[PDB]
Image 1 (cartoon, rainbow, N blue to C red):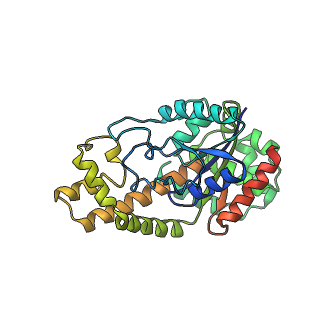
Image 2: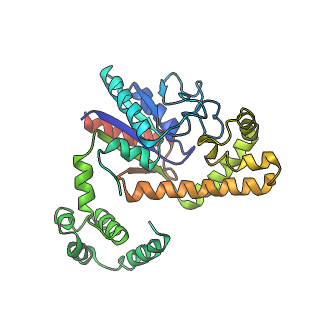
Image 3: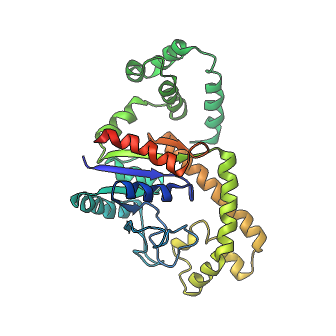
Length: 307
């Protein structure tokens, strides 16, 4: 299987910068995983990296279609698989920056996929009620459900044991099974890494990124797009455009709209963080404790094994 680096994380969380730094230390090339950066003309609302910021590193999947064009998880897979081969073929390191759960797993595994806020409380509450249990008592508990998991996971690795107990309690199904199928249907020798952070910092940064976008001409952009008739298009329905279109007509106030724009952005970021934790096995880097350089070292240590 071909080596592939995957760096997911919320918008402007450093995933983009980190990708380039990794690309510069291992002469690789980046494939944009964002399903919006594919449209030309939509640069501000999508946090599209500029040619200058790319620092020479070549990027793909950016400005490859017009707004009225259609895109999808598989469309991304078809194009990404070709680039990942071409890249490796030229002795380089294929790196995908960004992307959502669907787009990423659809690309990583060859299987058809298959979450209520209530279970969030039940599972979390029940887990916090499991903090009491010693290392072995909690292991026994895991054994009762997933024999295969508790079998190999040593009782002193509380982390992996909770992850298994956590997964079960939510989906109510086999955990060691997702492991198996994902382990066999995997197309690449993936090094999946994600940038994490507390909901507090996350939500605060998002509100701040929405302020900057407005300050950089986001509204002016949706104006040029809506004027070019690109309205009614799938792209114009993405968070950051669908909220502003109404205010351009005068049906909603800028204040109220922006209020909804920062909200949809917060919910979206959350939903994406949730998915990457309950479906993927990502090596999370806590952004609230590491820096661009510190992260590049965590990855450098991980890469000094694959070799």
